[PDB]
Length: 419
Image 1 (cartoon, rainbow, N blue to C red):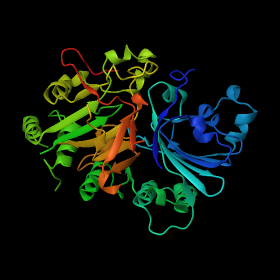
Image 2: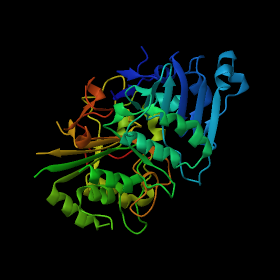
Image 3: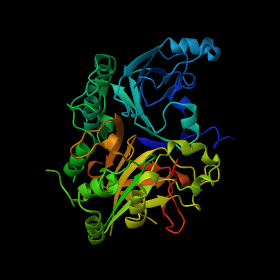
Image 4: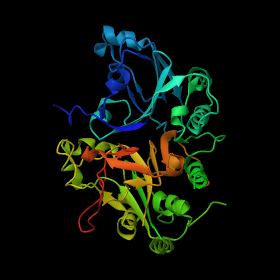
């Protein structure tokens, strides 16, 4: 079945887990179709076996690093000749952020993965990363297409590229997705013809269907305010209100929202590294470059989230391993827990995705996403509770890199890291 695994690091595991070599190094691997935001070609291609017949790479123009002659060799030369590139051009400040792997092996076997790291050595080894691995799939006629398969095809179709249609989608269509009948494929696309992002995700949660309402988000980037006039955060002012029913599509004042939260027992969480957590990371600030929250030019926005909603949470210093310490994770998780220490062991639903907490990744009720994003959704009424555990203590449906429980920011000294 599907399983979450923690990405091994050359630094943390110097002397269960997974590596890109485990994924691409198998002699039985026949073809790999890749999606990512950044490609370090010599690093990536060194992960494969000489037996591979084709490597189709989908990426944004300018994010694919060629291999210099001085760094080439006989082995790599062979791999390189099997690479086919499909470049996507995007408006400035828009991103093909999706990380996805579709492997085809000997016999009619196929497997799908969602790594949180882009394909570069630095990203793979510095921040903590995870990888969702689908159950083993096989080529063969299909009856009714599983929702996961149906959604994946819509996503691929939304690129509106002939190369994608013929070299990728046709191959995916031949695969039987029965083993994935319980999960959902959630995505974002800038396509004006395909609905996606928040709007689509909201509708899905509605269709899928006294207690404290826990809504937690773990992200590597935190977008700025949804408006230039007021301080409005995507999680606290739009997503949570929508999910709870406080609002419905055809933004309330901060204070009105705060009261609603109290009366409804809604508890918001955003896991993001503190300035001090890098001091207690094995590689110190080495992984800090991938965590972006620029609030210095609009301090009020930050103070609101930190003091008014008390939304920020950090790692439990007593539960993290010594080899990884308080090193932040570059994975993105969105989850909901209903109660009435143990919080989050059982979930109503959980989304693992490449999408950061920003308007560009999710869009809004009226605006569409600007990025390509992809993730997998686990929902209780589709499996009767989604089980989840923390890798920091290493069988559940979901496994997370952050500690469980997470600890609230000490309002007397904790501050979000600002690159």
